Image: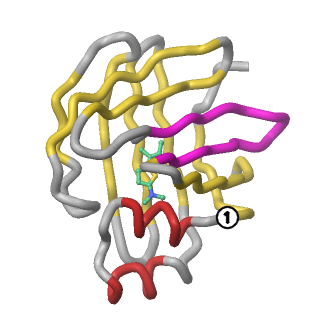
Amino acid sequence: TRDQNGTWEMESNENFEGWMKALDIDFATRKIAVRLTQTLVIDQDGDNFKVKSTSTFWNYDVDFTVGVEFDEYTKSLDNRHVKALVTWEGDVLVCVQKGEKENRGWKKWIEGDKLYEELTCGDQVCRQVFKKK
Ligand SMILES: *C/C=C(\C)c1ccc(N(C)C)s1
């Protein structure tokens, strides 16, 4: 199941604060951001993806082509330069962001009408579940 198209509304969020701490996000931002429900909008056509992560506090958008490395500035998240690559491991979409932080990236996959996400950085893992709206 590779079709991740849709507007995805958060149902569950685990260890989001630990992931933000691993990125060195400042105290004030974390305390506010950890409270918030997230939305994920994914536009997927072949290898081309357009991903938007939103809350009332942020809007993080990235476009990429599966299998094509891209240099990336992580902008309002943590203002770092990484070399990013998104690929398929079966039906798990896997992103690796090479740079200052170890084990940095994410994984997304579908189960039923839900989208599961792992956000990793350092020794931290944030687990999220979204429902298709
Ligand atoms: C596929 C998920 C992303 C590209 C995300 C970028 C920032 C996120 N959060 C702050 C939750 S998710």
Q: Which secondary structure lies at badge 1?
A: strand
Question: Dividing the image into 4 quarters, which one contains the N terminus?
Answer: top right
Q: Nearer the viewer, residue 72 or 59?
A: 72
In this picture, is 107 found above or below 40?
above
Residue to which mark 1 is pinned: 14
In this picture, is 17 found above or below 86?
below
**Residue at screen point 58% across, 72% down:** 37
Please report the bounds of the magenta region as a residue range: 105-120
Q: Is residue 115 magenta?
A: yes
Q: Where, by quadrant of the figure, is residue 126 drawn?
A: bottom right
Q: Amino acid at mark 1?
A: Glu
In this picture, is 121 found above or below 62?
below
Q: Where, by quadrant of the figure, is residue 58 drawn?
A: bottom left
> Residue 77 in the image: x percent, y percent?
28, 61
**Residue at screen point 66% across, 12% down:** 90
> Residue 45 in the image: x percent, y percent?
46, 18
Q: Where, by quadrant of the figure, is residue 62 drawn?
A: top left
Colour approach in the figure: secondary structure
